[PDB]
Image (cartoon, coloured by chain):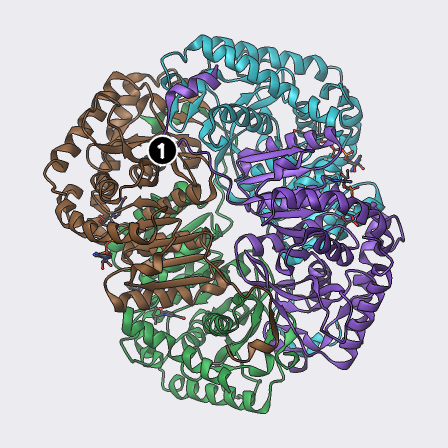
Chain colours: A brown, B cyan, C green, D purple
């Protein structure tokens, strides 16, 4: 057919060329495939590239996706081990690495996944020097810092998925108690994507009403008690799902599709994602953790530098100390 | 063909039946068609019915829409003057009536459009006793009250589009100054959909941060001054567009698609829409104005009764007095 | 507590607690069931999604994982459990439960195992949603659609097998890659068994309103289609993403009442010389009543012979089933 | 002020101020231009939408009305003005400006008026976006696509007329209503002039991969298609919604690089015995380079004769134009 379509088609552009929205996902595991599936459902890429080190699972996942192309708007889905396939990617989503066993801290994955990053990131930069890096692998705050150092990239193009998912979980749990859609409850989780994350009690809001304005009995103590209980469920959520299911995949897939949407579509939406926060909250080491960031086609265009409460800043400084305690021990 | 498809098709259900998401738009003017177009783009209806009193414009608009059905997911688009077409509608959007001339207050449309409603609403109720009424016609707060009285409906199924659009305008103007997407700036406008509407200064928020927490200099006076200027632009917006363009259509079309989405899809999202607020803010007459409401397939499932600031409650009481000053003079 | 204060800062206007209007149940939270659930959620088809299985822990873990992405969805209630009372009044029930293929194993070899599973599932589905649409995905999909019809007592319009919607998608993708166009503009039909004896309707091939004759190896492509599942199973262990997307496609047409045409499994006795109660894929019109119309196409002699053989291959396994 | 404080509560990480990656310009903010703009906005195709016209007040009013719905959109910059510097570096330029039909008036009678308008528009477009794709909508679309090609000096792949994408949609809708299926599963092509001499490709008709022959009055339907615009113009004064949706459809394929097939206006010299530089609708493959491929179909004798006549009818008006 490649021989005979040459005479019921007139070619007007002898020069086919690159894709304008090429997205690469590294790692075709549970998280990688959920991210790729969410990115495809959002119609964000005209070319999707999958990279891994297990050839047979790579090819099977690729074929499975490819074969649903009737139902999608991504005309090129490709997969392999050779980073040449990723050349000139707009966005590279790194999901590769060790994941938590039951009861295991994300921080206990750091040495295994730094070693993996030492190989992945140089190869990414080689073929896509201008891409945005979106880090998902845990521990995400440390591996975003690591990716930043290994890549030589400016801060705007090295992003960790961070607390976008923790914040979505938090907003789900609170809106569940009220009986409204999570999109109309506003609250954010900042700091470590882990046990030391920080609820921003001062900013809880429903559809343009400060939480304190809903009811006379919703005072500072009520809010501290509520969030004490809700935040415990947030920090525990991943552990319980790992005990029950083995891993998490669907919610982070949706979160990464959310972040990719703002990045690819240049929306300048605000997300709590991992970036360098030296200079904020009394932090003086080169620690990355989640703060609100404006996202668009240049990556992080702006970082918020808010004036939060004394307690919130101190909890964030403590979160940075926890990260640094692990980060100081890695060798690059 | 209706004769010959009878032998390359086997009918398995001799009994075709009603539509599950039948939506009627009354009025095929600028607002009605923008609403119908937005409802179609959201794929909310399997049957869309258009009602008006001008037969030729009715048929032309119907055909124009019908002919783009390849690109839509609404298999039945129909139009006419006979309310029998609307039978068993889930949702009825009323956009019919006089609109503002240059400089004209929405309240100056009340007698003309009450008279129009005296004919429309009884006919709607006759063929769709269980529908949700969504009132768009101005002055929207008074005509929602009027529709409530004429219909005999419970409060949950009589909704005015209210300040959903005013709030969208407000969030656009503020987020424009910051340089972020309006979806991440949270602020609401309540009260009259008109000159006496009320910005809720106490609830301004960016992506889970209270506005006061962005910068030490953002204090109560800064916020009052900012909103003084922004709110003036909000109340003026419709007048300027009417002077320049003759009318407004696109933003209210999108707003009504937003409200219809929450209603049809049962999302329990919160919108500032017009409902009865006797019993709130010191209001003791049967005044409708915009307060935050939970919307789903039963219409308004819940109304927020917030504890706003003294000034906000007083501005809302004044807004209700302004509405009542006009509403007391209509005869039903 | 926020549970107690909401009782005071919200005024309920309705003391009615109606039922969801687009309640969708997925039976089986395996690889296929979750891919189906995820696609249905992405298409915003349900205001209530129910997941049923027999492994409590995996159920709850999958439910929690989906729930926690609710901010990015338009489905306000996601629930999971073992009790079919959770499924009551479902509009659509997608059955993905059962044994799946090992490497190189015919789908037909699964049938007696999955008949046994269906003898439990279907009567429990019908007890709580007697007016629902059944969409069968478990293999072998053509026989198990027949089984579901017999156990449920439903009319034929409300018992549908996912059939060759997926096989056709694969066919259209493969041909479209050779031409260099998007698969939605290549129109090619695969009918018959979802399996080794499927039939490409080469007489119907068309590009954007041009018949082939307006413009051998299309049999070669069909062979790649029949082998595709085996290849992926060998490489990956199973398939999930394409069938999830195909089920979401079918679900869209059913839930949104689109009257779209899909090659799905339904009774074809009376067509192509088939006198036994065999289900296989023919094109059907799908909407909120299920299959409203079935196409009676006049195919070539070779194509109707190939369909009769397909029916005989199915019947050869179906006839041995104790039901 | 909030303008001054944002300078302090945000840290800029980029002092680069790049250019939008999907900048779309619509020339003409009349009924067609705004319906096109609204559909493009609903499809979230552009991060920057530019509206150009020559009536300052209506421009600003339409811009403000669109802008104020931004919360419900995914287009962060919407701008409008008279100055083509606003359009710089546009990926796609949709030209809807010009005279439209009065009741009963041939589209061909508009051409000399709209050629004059194009002699101003096109050189200004090309000055500021030399690499853009031109999508011509103004009537008569087939001649004005030729005109745009000649004035712009663009290659043929980047000068596209909306052509019979709309006429085909109308044809498919009308036939689909008689059968009772969704129009996306009926495949029928209308080629030639967007106008009175269009040509139904009855040899290519197909339902979901079944040729008609697998299953007179399809000429009757085509007559309803040619008359449809006149009827709506008589009833409503103009048309807008269907062409807006059709332009959004074409724009989707171009902007998202889908390689979908549409019947659009392009040069057909060398086909169907046409020796003049006539543009009319044939099926074309659309992506981010514009038209990458044009179909050379082998139609029936009656269909190629009907296309030649269509070409002659177009040429009869086109030959009289001073350019
Ligand atoms: N940031 C979050 O919110 C979040 C949520 C869930 C999981 N995670 C993390 O995502 C990561 C992956 O989790 P998972 O469930 O997908 O695990 P998984 O076991 O399913 O997949 C991991 C993939 O990484 C591949 N891989 C390993 N080394 C590689 C290398 N040098 N190059 C390319 N690919 C390589 C593996 O072959 C494997 O396919 C883990 O670190 C997990 O902790 C993060
Ligand atoms: N709530 C809002 O935010 C908002 C925004 C914009 C406009 N509006 C209001 O929407 C209403 C319509 O505005 P428009 O721009 O579409 O005006 P329009 O002139 O374009 O259309 C009004 C339509 O109402 C029809 N109509 C009149 N009487 C009727 C009757 N008894 N039954 C059925 N149809 C009847 C008319 O034939 C006409 O087609 C006005 O009241 C306007 O003030 C409200
Ligand atoms: N029609 C198609 O195109 C297609 C495509 C792929 C797979 N399949 C078939 O789908 C079915 C499932 O495949 P899979 O990969 O998800 O397998 P899986 O093993 O991953 O999941 C199977 C699920 O079925 C559950 N189950 C078993 N008995 C049950 C019962 N009485 N009630 C409720 N749930 C029960 C299991 O606990 C398990 O969770 C198989 O039959 C497979 O062959 C069909
Ligand atoms: N291809 C199709 O299928 C199709 C369908 C419908 C209409 N049309 C055609 O689209 C064109 C516009 O139709 P309409 O209903 O929007 O007319 P309209 O009168 O409502 O709008 C025409 C716009 O063109 C503007 N304009 C005039 N000169 C201009 C110039 N130098 N530069 C920029 N703008 C200029 C006008 O100011 C006006 O705003 C007509 O030619 C019509 O026949 C084509």
The residue located at (67%, 26%) in the rendering is: B140
- Looking at the picture, how far across and down is residue D32, in whole percent? 73, 45
Quadrant that contains the C terminus of chain A: top left
Describe residue C275's horizontal placement relative to residue B91 as left or right.
left
Q: Is residue B171 above or below residue C232?
A: above
Q: Residues within 10 Å of mark 1 (few under 14, many from 20)?
A: some
* Chain of the residue where label 1 is placed in the rendered structure: A
Q: Is residue D91 visible?
A: yes
- Looking at the picture, how far across and down is residue B113, in whole percent? 77, 27
Q: Nearer the viewer, residue A250 or B174?
A: B174
Q: Is residue A329 above or below residue B217?
A: below
Q: Nearer the viewer, residue D254 or B145?
A: D254
The residue located at (74%, 47%) in the rendering is: D240
Q: Is residue B157 visible?
A: no
Quarter of the image for residue A176 reads top left
Residue at the limit of the structure toward the right, as seen here: D104
Q: Is residue C151 above or below residue A53?
A: below
Describe residue C192's horizontal placement relative to residue B79 as left or right.
left
Q: Is mark 1 within 8 Å of ligand 1?
A: no
- Looking at the picture, how far across and down is residue A141, in whole percent? 23, 38
Describe residue B306's horizontal placement relative to residue C33 as left or right.
right
Count the labels in the image: 1
Quarter of the image for residue D157 reads bottom right
Under tag 1, what secondary structure? Answer: helix
- Looking at the picture, how far across and down is residue C144, in whole percent? 40, 74
Q: Nearer the viewer, residue B1 or A121?
A: A121
The residue located at (44%, 84%) in the rendering is: C197
Mark 1, residue position: A177
The residue located at (55%, 75%) in the rendering is: C188
């Amino acid at each position: 057919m490649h021989s005979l379509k040459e005479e019921f088609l007139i070619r007007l552009t002898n020069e086919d060329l690159n894709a304008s929205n090429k997205i690469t996902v590294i790692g075709v595991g549970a998280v990688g495939m959920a991210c790729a599936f969410s990115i495809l459902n959002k119609e964000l890429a005209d070319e999707l590239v999958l990279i891994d080190v297990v050839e047979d699972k790579l090819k099977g996942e690729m074929m499975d996706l490819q074969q649903g192309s009737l139902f999608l708007k991504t005309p090129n889905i490709i997969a392999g081990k050779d980073y040449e396939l990723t050349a000139n990617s707009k966005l590279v989503v790194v999901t590769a690495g060790a994941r938590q066993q039951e009861g295991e801290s994300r921080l206990n994955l750091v040495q295994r996944n730094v070693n993996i990053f030492k190989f992945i990131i140089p190869n990414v930069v080689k073929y896509s020097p201008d891409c945005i890096l979106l880090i998902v692998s845990n521990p995400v705050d440390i591996l975003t810092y690591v990716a930043w150092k290994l890549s030589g990239f400016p801060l705007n193009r090295v992003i960790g998925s961070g607390c976008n998912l923790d914040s979505a979980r938090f907003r789900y749990l609170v809106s569940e108690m009220i009986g409204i859609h999570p999109s109309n409850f506003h609250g954010c989780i900042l700091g470590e994507h882990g046990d030391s994350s920080v609820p921003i009690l001062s900013g809880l809001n429903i559809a343009g009403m400060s939480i304190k304005n809903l009811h006379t009995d919703i005072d500072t103590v009520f809010i501290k008690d509520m969030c004490k209980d809700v935040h415990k469920k947030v920090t525990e959520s991943a552990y319980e799902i790992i005990k029950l299911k083995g891993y998490t995949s669907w919610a982070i897939g949706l979160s990464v599709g959310d972040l990719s949407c703002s990045l690819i579509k240049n929306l300048r939406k605000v997300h709590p994602v991992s970036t360098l926060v030296k200079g904020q909250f009394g932090i003086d080491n080169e620690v990355f953790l989640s703060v609100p960031c404006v996202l668009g086609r240049n990556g992080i265009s702006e970082v918020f530098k808010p004036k939060l409460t004394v307690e919130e800043e101190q909890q964030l400084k403590n979160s940075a100390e926890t990260i640094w305690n692990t980060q100081k021990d890695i060798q690059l």
